[PDB]
Image: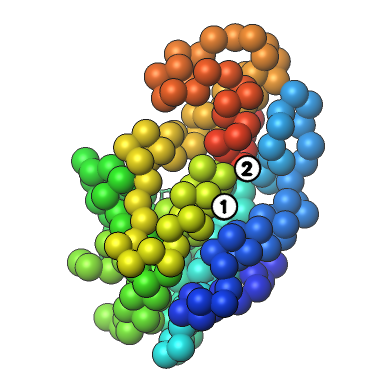
Amino acid sequence: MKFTEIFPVEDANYPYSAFIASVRKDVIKHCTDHKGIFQPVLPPEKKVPELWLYTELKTRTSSITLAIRMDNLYLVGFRTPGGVWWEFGKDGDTHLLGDNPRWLGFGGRYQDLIGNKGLETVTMGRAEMTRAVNDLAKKKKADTKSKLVKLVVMVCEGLRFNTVSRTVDAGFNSQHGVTLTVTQGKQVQKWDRISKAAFEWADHPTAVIPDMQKLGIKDKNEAARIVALVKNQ
Ligand SMILES: Nc1ncnc2[nH]cnc12
């Protein structure tokens, strides 16, 4: 239950880099040092998550609160200014949130938000993220998918990958915005697997793992500079 330092998205005086930095520091307070594994290993998964990361994003005009589960740096939902909670999911699923919330209608996976398509297409940046927040706070009750998917890569994958927090910070104030490279996306969509190989590599640092080979990742060394935070078991 750690509340994140507010991130003034519209205020160009705050870097994207600090936001991330600040958050990981918070997150890490809860990770464990595993042998042979470079990166801090996240809290172990539980059907009902224990530790949560409440990270609010505010603009000149509005703000929303992000509900992310630590165990796997996944965005479970958000909060509108008026105190309403939207959770990824359909009627019948089980809730994890947080004060009477209203199933968003769709899950929060890439296939769900933009199936068959690659992260290289989701455009991101301070602007895009400002557009996103304001737009998502003006929500009552599907172009709020394209809005969530930006925050998903910007915030969630930014927390998970150095490779993302670097390409995003570098192009955050770009007019044309910033997008990941084909390869990055693929890699980003394989967080789960890279992580598993981080464990595999702790045991056999030598083992060649075609899945990582197939992603442009040679060894545990290369993966270490890509992923910041790892997963499980
Ligand atoms: N909603 C989400 N939050 C964090 N990471 C994700 N990867 C795919 N969907 C995600």
The structure residue drawn at horizontal position 64% and vertical position 18%, both measured from the top left corner, is 201
Describe the element under mark 2 as helix, strand or loop.
loop
Residue holding disc 2: 229
The N terminus, quarter of image: bottom right
Q: What colouring style does the render use?
A: rainbow
Verify CB contact (< 8 Å) between mark 2 and mark 1: yes
Above or below residue 80? Residue 189 is: above
Above or below residue 209? Residue 25 is: below
* Mark nearer the N terminus (2 vs 1): 1
Residue holding disc 1: 159
The structure residue drawn at horizontal position 63% and vertical position 64%, both measured from the top left corner, is 18
The reply to whether residue 75 is in sight is no
- In percent of width and height, residue 5 lies at 65, 73
Above or below residue 73? Residue 212 is: above
Task: Give how far apart the Cα atoms at labels 2 and 1 are.
Answer: 7 Å
- In percent of width and height, residue 170 lies at 48, 55
> Pointer 2: residues within 10 angstroms few (<14), some, or many (20+)?
many
> Pointer 1: residues within 10 angstroms few (<14), some, or many (20+)?
many
The structure residue drawn at horizontal position 52% and vertical position 29%, both measured from the top left corner, is 194
Residue situated in front as seen by the camera: 199 or 128:
128
Residue situated in front as seen by the camera: 98 or 23:
23
